[PDB]
Amino acid sequence: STGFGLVYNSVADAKKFEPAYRLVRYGLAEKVEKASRQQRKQRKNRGKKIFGTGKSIAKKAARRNAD
Amino acid sequence: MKLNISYPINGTQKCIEIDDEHRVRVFYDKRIGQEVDGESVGDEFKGYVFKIAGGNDKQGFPMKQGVLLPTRVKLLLAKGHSCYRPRRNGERKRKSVRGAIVGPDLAVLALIITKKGEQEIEGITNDTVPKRLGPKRANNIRKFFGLTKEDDVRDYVIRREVTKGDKSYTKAPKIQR
Amino acid sequence: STELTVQSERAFQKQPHIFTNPKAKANRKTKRWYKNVGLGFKTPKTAIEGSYIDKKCPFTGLVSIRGKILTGTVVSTRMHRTIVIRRDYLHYVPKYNRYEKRHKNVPAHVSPAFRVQVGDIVTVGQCRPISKTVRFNVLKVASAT
Amino acid sequence: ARGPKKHLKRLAAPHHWMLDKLSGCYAPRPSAGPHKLRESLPLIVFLRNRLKYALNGREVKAILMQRHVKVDGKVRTDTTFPAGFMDVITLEATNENFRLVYDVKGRFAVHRITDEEASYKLAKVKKVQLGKKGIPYVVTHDGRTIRYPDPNIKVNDTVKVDLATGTITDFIKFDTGKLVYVTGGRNLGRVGTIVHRERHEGGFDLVHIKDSLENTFVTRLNNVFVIGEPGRPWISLPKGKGIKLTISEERDRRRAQHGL
RNA sequence: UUCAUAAUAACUUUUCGAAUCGCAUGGCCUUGUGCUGGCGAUGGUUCAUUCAAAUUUCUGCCCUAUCAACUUUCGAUGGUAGGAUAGUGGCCUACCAUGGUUUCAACGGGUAACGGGGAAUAAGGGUUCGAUUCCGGAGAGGGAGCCUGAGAAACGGCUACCA
RNA sequence: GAAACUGCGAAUGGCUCAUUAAAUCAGUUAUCGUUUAUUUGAUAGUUCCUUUACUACAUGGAUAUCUGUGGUAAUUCUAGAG
């Protein structure tokens, strides 16, 4: 077989330059848990809808119940 | 119907509900931006001088001034004149809008209250709320305290001390220029 | 091809930004400017001695000759200061291994210095868009008798 | 229609980049600069595919930020700067200096220059024009404009530049019996000594050119670039020396030249 | 070249000619909080260069005579003078001149027609196809019309009418 | 440093073949007939307007975000004041 090896100088140098997924497999850095591609795309659209912040519209929610 | 009252100097506002027509009949055939007396409105206000300038319609049609008529005329709006917030820079949009002169079609009336009268009510003329944001620039901080040049700055600054629980660390503005 | 009258319009015509000095005293009166066309051509003295102005003339005007230099025989002559050069040529047909003959005409503007008739060869040079169809100007009339 | 174009499909890109057919849909568009789209060479191609330090375009962006690339003295952190002919590319780490000179085939060559000689750049003219306050200023064909030239410098005449400071040092005149490089068309990356010049009346000038082997070839004027006295090169040239050989001559060399 | 560029005469509801900010905190003191000074950001005027964009020269197209005359009122072809245009031009008006294309096939009709680089078949010549991975051009349900920006008659932007 | 103001981009990419027969398009030309953000290059003592009492040691007021008072069957609807 024929690999493709990279021998860095030190540990602090090899941590930053190498891609994140390569650090996971050997067990150097932590695995970055993130949200699914669908739901965070929905969050972008729903965040855009309300001009915002959530304070002003939430205070109206109490007033809208009386109507 | 509802009256949006707001005192400018003190800084307190309240909605007064009016089911009776006779009280609102003073505002019939009166235009946006004129002085109105308090005595003819009702028993609550006597000695006051109201200031009608704005309004609101049933369904949801904010009133614009300079339009004339007692009608709902659709108008062409853009950046520079109110009743439209543009999203694209330069884009226009034809919006619906309520006319100027008041009739029996409204839900809320806009009112500023200049001069006091007799019956000071609960928390509209009694209470006085301070303004939230202090000065900032070089000549705004100078004129507020009446300092002129030689008195210098780095002295008259508001440091609000907020507490999470144990600590009491200071905040501070940033005097630009 | 009017011609001869010098001035006969509603307006008046002079060469732009060339001035006749009123106080100075010389035989000229009419102050003429004329240009060298280039590309190894020869400007005639009928243009220099003449009285015509013309915006669209290459000798006395802003029309600069550049690009291509076509040729051909003249056909049509019957309008004010233009000409139609008929340029004949052959076209190939690979299937039969033969040649064709094709036609299309070329319109051009004439300087009043040159004297033109029907059935004479005319060398012609490309220039600014003079008009709708006319994109060319006359530079020679070598009518061998 | 509608404004500029900010993409380049890989088959539509010029061939002397030497990019792969597979392993990518798009190619790197070189941005605006002192060199044209066809004649330039972007820094992604130079670092990734030529020198072969970085494996992909990701790692080229890491090198530029920390931070030793120097095209014509100054840094440039842009990934796709149009670096072209006679441009000096230095590296403080490794102590390497380069110059983009054309190969006998037509490609850009990886030519390792001395420390040392990488210091002056050679450019062409161009104009030859007066500015305001009657100031005479010269333009370079390879990018820049320089002020206050010598009174006898004209079109197609090459000029040496200081690079670090940015001023004129010396000039060479375009006349017969002098070395000249070619940077356009089919006879690209060849060197020769000149014989004749057909001037013509507004229809492109031509030049007849020999070489050390006495083989003749003809090219256009705008492609030609002067490079010193005959048998006296101002700049260091790579192996080959712009000779250009026959098909059968090159077959003879490779199978003969062996030694494992 | 009436080009580059310079000079004289003035104009203009007089464009621009830095009231902008981070990392360092040095040098002789006229030892002020002043006279000078390092490393990069940003904005700006005219002239270059680059990415382009507009028009433009020459030659080249599939069937049809059961399409031989066609355009000029309502610009057709040309001249002079203005208007508009980023800029040339009948692009648009005013007063004139009657021209332009045509059996070397104009003008009209049809196309189950987007144009090329190409593909299929394969003695040599040629036949037939090219909606479609690259290059250029049109269009966003059908037509007109614009706003903002260097660049849009934008449509994952707007104002109408007809579905 | 959430939010919003200013600046930039959204005119590229992607999809389709309805129209169109000297039109589009291909190869050759000219822009001495014009506009170009961005790009990398150069570059502005000349605004003062008689030259003894003139802002130049630095000028002016808003507007957001947020504080709240709301209406609406409705929608990235936006009215009043601070």
Image (tube, coloured by chain):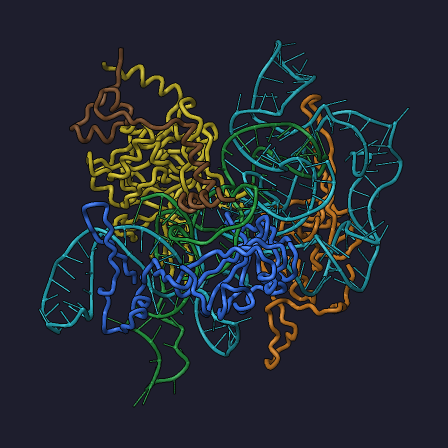
Chain colours: A brown, B blue, C orange, D yellow, E cyan, F green
Can residue B69 be seen in the rendering of this structure?
A: yes
Residue E44: x and y in percent read 41, 59
- What residue is at 49 percent from the left and 69 percent from the top? B48
Specify the quadrant of the image occupied by residue A31: top left
Going 69% across and 26% down the picture, which residue do you hit?
C93
Residue nearest the viewer, comparing D60 with D53: D60
Q: Which quarter shows the N terminus of chain D?
A: top right
- x and y percent of residue B9 in the render? 40, 66
The quadrant of the image that shows the C terminus of chain D is top left
* Residue name at image x 29 percent, y 60 percent: B176
Position in image of residue F80 (x %, y %):
49, 60
Residue D42 in which image quadrant: top left
Q: Quadrant of residue B40?
A: bottom right
The count of marks equals 0
Tell me: residue B32, above or below residue D232: below
**Lateral position of residue D207 relative to residue E127, left or right:** left
* Front-most of residues F55 and C110: F55
Q: Is residue D120 above or below residue E45?
A: above
Name of the residue lying farthest toward the front: B43
Residue situated in front as seen by the camera: B156 or D166: B156
Residue located 23% across and 49% down the image:
B163
- In this rendering, the answer to whether C84 lies above or below E104 is below
Q: Is residue C46 visible?
A: no
Q: Position of residue B177 (x, y in %)?
A: 29, 63
Tell me if F34 is positioned left or right of B168 in this view.
right
